[PDB]
Amino acid sequence: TNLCPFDEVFNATRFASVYAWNRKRISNCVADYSVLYNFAPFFAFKCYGVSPTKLNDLCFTNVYADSFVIRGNEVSQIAPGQTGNIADYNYKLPDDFTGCVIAWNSNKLDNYLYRLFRKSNLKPFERDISTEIYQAGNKPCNGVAGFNCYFPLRSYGFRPTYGVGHQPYRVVVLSFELLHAPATVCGPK
Amino acid sequence: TNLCPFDEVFNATRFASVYAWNRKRISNCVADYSVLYNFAPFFAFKCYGVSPTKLNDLCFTNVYADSFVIRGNEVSQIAPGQTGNIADYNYKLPDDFTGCVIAWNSNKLDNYLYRLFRKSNLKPFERDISTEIYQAGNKPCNGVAGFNCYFPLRSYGFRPTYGVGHQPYRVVVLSFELLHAPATVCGPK
Amino acid sequence: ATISWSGQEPAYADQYTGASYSILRDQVGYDY
Amino acid sequence: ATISWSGQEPAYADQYTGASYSILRDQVGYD
């Protein structure tokens, strides 16, 4: 019993942005992977490292799930560390990290935001919710937009039939964290 | 002897603006290169290739002077072979021309506008008036100001008692050109 | 017809060796 | 206070590729 929400947090309406995610910890519960492992058609799957066929057996201290609506072909960027504008600015997964990502296209379901380049490369696992002015030029722009003054974030709102490769994708990342002295959170019996 | 007129164009009451700078063509006449230099105290007479002799020996087919206004720390870009949209996005001179640049202060004398992002750089010697809204993002602003959509023009403030760097003074660029149909020239006294 | 190139578990409908996967169910999975 | 590379005489009060050094009667130029 006491199944994790899983489906609810995955079938959730009004999905969040991409530059500003919402890391949700999943607390002590018994989580069957059948609904995630097997689904309605489409709904691609891309799981690295450790595989469910033995996660059904072993136990994990705790897990985090993050959700976002990244569009385009850059869904390849969520993979072992690859240099690409999405990766180093809309956060990069660490190489040693062995969680799994599941993506599928969203057109029937769907004004949205997309993070622009930062002043420097960014380490994994920190949010960059931030509205300031990017200082490209040596001349301190220190205010409203001008030469080398770019306000981050972009949009693609209301884009029906923009191209089969351009359709709105959405993807979710799961990370299994094993802190010292495990407590709970096992597989189904 | 219909002396070639310079007092009216330097001592003009309404000096116009850098956004819409009044190009003034001067017809055939005889100049007095004595008032040109040693003008009112303090001024700039930067030029490239000007010895007074070859000015006074003979005069040329025609001349198209230009006049405009900027603050203190931007007289670098009016000189040719320079970048910086502070003046590049409003003016630009070729590397081959041989005119002069004249500067004089107007703090005592004194709403004015400022050029801002333009779709692309302009060659030497065009004209651009544009109330049409500029865009730097993907969403078409197509109307009033919005995300990434800004008013294409900006003011100068002309605030008195501002800093020595942050005060305006005006500039006239003088171009001497000899063109085709040589049988017009110009005659010394 | 999906199929898994990584030596095991073919997949049926109605590249590169990184690790264990199950991908390319849609048309996004490949690059060429 | 200002040395002219062209060798012509500067004007007495009471860095780029330029030709005439009958200039710099003001504090606009120089570092």
Image: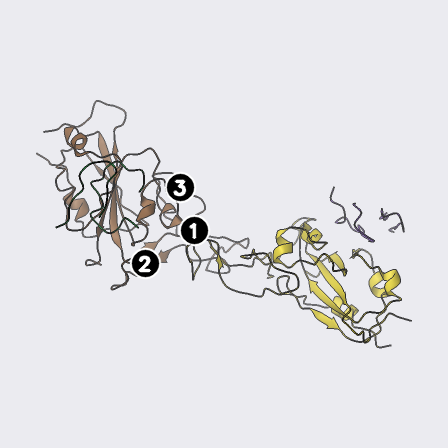
Chain colours: A yellow, B brown, C purple, D green
Real-space Cα separation, disc 2 to disc 3, in angstroms: 22 Å
In front of the other: A136 or B22 = A136
Q: Of label 2 and label 3, which has the lower sequence position?
A: 3
In what element is the residue under mark 1? Answer: loop
Badge 1: few (under 14), some or many (20 or more) residues near its Cα, within 10 Å?
Answer: some
Residue drawn at x 56%, y 59% as measured from the top left: A153
In front of the other: A118 or B3 = A118
In the picture of the structure, the residue carrying the numbered disc 1 is B117
Report the number of discs: 3
Q: Is residue C31 left or right of residue B154?
A: right
Residue A23 image offset from top left, x and y in percent:
69, 68
In the picture of the structure, the residue carrying the numbered disc 2 is B156
Badge 3: few (under 14), some or many (20 or more) residues near its Cα, within 10 Å?
Answer: some
**On-image quarter of the N terminus of chain A:** bottom right
Asked whether the beta carbons under mark 3 and mark 1 sit within 8 Å of each other, the answer is no
Residue A22 image offset from top left, x and y in percent:
67, 68
